[PDB]
Image (cartoon, rainbow over all chains, first blue to last red; front, side, top):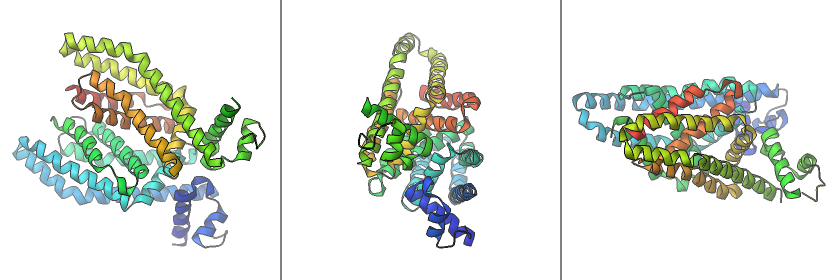
Length: 198
Length: 198
């Protein structure tokens, strides 16, 4: 918990004053502890390990929350292939609701993910984590496309990932009062219609 | 040119030591001029105005270089709709060659674009530019999808943009000797096949 405060403090600094303001002093400052209590690069690495872990856990929770819906959708399609049009309506609403909650409720976590991504480029110590991270992102989308009978579930999962990351970034730039929720729906819908043959 | 050195120097600092190391001293240092010669936020803003302008101009040059190919492809499709399969082969190769040259030849410019994107989030002075910039990105892709008879050229242009940005980021992380060129082809191809009805 001592450990976790420090990490959490390093995080806040990262959101606020960027990566470059993570030093032991500014950090021990921020977590409210002595210097010693707080290898600056081990701290940075741990911080971004935590950010990755929280994203991974929230995405697990998300996929877990729609597991039942995905199960019902697959049964509906087995009885009635003509239900594709209908399914996509459901999928798009669930997806945009995902992004919305991320961009409103989890803004600082997303902001910390943007700092990590920016950082991974410059830091060889972080390329390990960053490939762990891009492999985690696509892999939930994979079961979703497989469950729906997509022709190429791995490539669809990557395209999906690409679209959602850009939507997230653009929502962070637009801000919470001006989310382009109908544009997000249209973009997602165009892609998913195509996957489904519509 | 005095102006341009300074801007260019602010750039190099941004690639190297991030946004936070842009100060008049560190900059006048880097451009090799006196402090006075070099409102720190006007400098930052100008720097990122330049980065945007160079990206915009290189993308214009790219689209200009394939104009003829796009013209021939459209004629081929008018005579022979069954040529879709063939066209996509051509389009994917031209696209991946784009990303490749960007990721090898223009690495530092792409790195500076990643710093800008990271910055736009925190800086209200930059949200103007950043929306200029996301509107420029999609708009070339639009003529391309229109020229090919895409069902929804504006949404396709955004999806395309999303895929290419993520490919660029992932190539910066992988590095020039380990570009995942065949994975890029497969991802792009999956999307373009879908747009073309394949």
